[PDB]
Amino acid sequence: KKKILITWPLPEAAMARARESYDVIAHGDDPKITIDEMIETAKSVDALLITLNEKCRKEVIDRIPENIKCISTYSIGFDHIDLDACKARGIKVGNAPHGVTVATAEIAMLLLLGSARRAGEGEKMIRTRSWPGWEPLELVGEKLDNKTLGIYGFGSIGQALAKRAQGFDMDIDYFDTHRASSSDEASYQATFHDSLDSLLSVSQFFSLNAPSTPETRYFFNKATIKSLPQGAIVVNTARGDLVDNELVVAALEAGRLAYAGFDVFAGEPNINEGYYDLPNTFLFPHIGSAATQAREDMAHQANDLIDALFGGADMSYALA
Amino acid sequence: KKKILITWPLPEAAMARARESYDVIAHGDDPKITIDEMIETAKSVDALLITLNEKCRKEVIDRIPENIKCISTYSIGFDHIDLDACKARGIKVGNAPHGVTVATAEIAMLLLLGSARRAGEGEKMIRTRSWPGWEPLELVGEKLDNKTLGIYGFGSIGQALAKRAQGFDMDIDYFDTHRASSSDEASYQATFHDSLDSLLSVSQFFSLNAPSTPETRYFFNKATIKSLPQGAIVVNTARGDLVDNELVVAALEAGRLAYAGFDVFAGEPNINEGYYDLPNTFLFPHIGSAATQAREDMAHQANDLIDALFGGADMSYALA
């Protein structure tokens, strides 16, 4: 029975497969694993299963016990792992890049609906016990049906958003540098725009599902906001650094933007302090893939990786 | 210009039409209208536009000056008007009963979604600055796709809901007293249940869209709850007296029900005190029809009834 260190508690179905295959050292999270704990514990274990929370920079990869020739990361990304360093040392890394499409689409829909319908301010009025009863002008939002949704980025997640968005009778327009199949645009009656500027124009609702690129970093800013229709509503579930916070906070205040629904922020969890008191925001602590079905696919996937190192085959989601 | 009293501030478009055709006394919500003030002011005007907040029962219809033979209620119901006493005294009464179907279906879908995805808890974590950053078990809920939705009451709102739910890939099973036409059912691949019980049994998510009626009043109680799957989620946008508050607070606390998303409460705004603290609830201050598109259809309809009275024609939404 090979031994593995699991740095954080995962969903029970994941943990249980792990314990039916390995001698697991499961760490809790109260006082999360410090890297030095990992480096230490690493010596009694054959393999690591880490989260994006363990930042394995070159320095740390070089500090790792030579016992370990396997790191599975419970994540879609690997921004926290030096894959070069791992590769030179012959440390094989894999990841868990599936099972989060629908879950994220759902949250993008939720944020669009909750923003049109002022759910955050609703919740507050009740919890805070400041509800005087129904009046005709109290927390009045707007309906989604026959409003235009501009989706920037029309891949798996942007497409599943369009599915859930056509159920509310929204009109779906998009821009991506990859134009989807005709068979596909038809599926959603999605209108392609060959330019971002062309899309911002028609976008009463705007969804950032775009890939982060140095060139697209902070693109959502003052100049981009002024191309949106007045009182436009923007949601972001992609990458917090696609948005320039100062300019978003300023337009929400000016009403240039009606509402914002953000799942991800630049600098999370130390999000720009302006967000906290803005009443026209609906804000989540990165719970895009926070669904049990998603969180277990990721875990079974991170387990598949380990399985295939110890089985002597190629890692199913081979990063290194 | 015939004078009218409008008891509450209404949307901007409706107020504008009102003051086009009428000399309007507009009463603010600052210190809301009291009955006496309404009675005193009815002497100086030709008709009343009131809301559901003005309870015009017999003892108040008794006080009404002989000049008022017109009453329009910005409201879908008329529980607050003694329609008899009105007929007896020759007072013609109409309501505004359209333009809330989609708005309410949206709010029912938002509560199903924000419940599965624990949206109230997210907003609370951000706003309180209690967010430690992403972790695999932070605020994990469940996806809606391929889950079964049970709808109690397949009217207009029930079917705008099934539409919006089949976009999230839910399976709609339903119970209504009069089974729906063969074509409705196909629209939504809905599955008919010949009893509420055989419906309750399959309902991982459950939506009360039933009418408030002697037999349905307080129908949702411990014996119904136990008939649902373990940890089902229940939303109610219909009426608060359809739900036995004591037995839902208990079952939510047991975990017998996972979540409840409610728009309406027995006693609102004086809702059961044991809701405020429950973390597995997503709760709104009754904003099922709080979209500016609905709120304005409603006041145009309410103005319609007054145009007809002064025209010699029947009110379009004649109650009495």
Image (spheres, coloured by chain):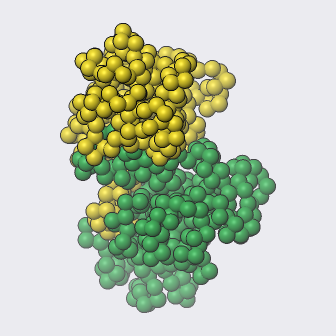
Chain colours: A yellow, B green
Using the image, determine if residue A55 lies above or below residue A33.
above
Using the image, determine if residue A105 lies above or below residue B187.
above
Tell me the quadrant of the picture where the C terminus of chain A can be found. Answer: top left
- In the image: residue B243, left or right of residue B1: right
Single out the residue that lies furthest toward the top. Answer: A88
For the point 46% across and 54% down, the residue is B115
Q: Nearer the viewer, residue B212 or A317?
A: A317
- Residue B38 appears in the rendering: yes
On the image, the x and y values in percent for residue A107 come to 45, 41
Q: Nearer the viewer, residue B71 or B35?
A: B35
For the point 29% across and 66% down, the residue is A129
For the point 41% across and 86% down, the residue is B60
Single out the residue that lies furthest toward the left. Answer: A273
On the image, the x and y values in percent for residue A278 come to 25, 45
On the image, the x and y values in percent for residue B310 come to 51, 69
Using the image, determine if residue A204 lies above or below residue A211.
below
For the point 31% across and 43% down, the residue is A29
Task: Kindly indicate the quadrant of the structure image that contains residue A260.
Answer: top left
Say how many tags the image has.
Answer: 0
Task: Kindly indicate the quadrant of the structure image that contains residue A220.
Answer: top left
Q: Nearer the viewer, residue B299 or A253?
A: A253
Q: Nearer the viewer, residue B169 or A31?
A: A31
Task: Kindly indicate the quadrant of the structure image that contains residue B61.
Answer: bottom left
- Residue B20 appears in the rendering: no
- In the image: residue B220, left or right of residue B68: right
On the image, the x and y values in percent for residue B297 come to 50, 56
Using the image, determine if residue A37 lies above or below residue A29.
above
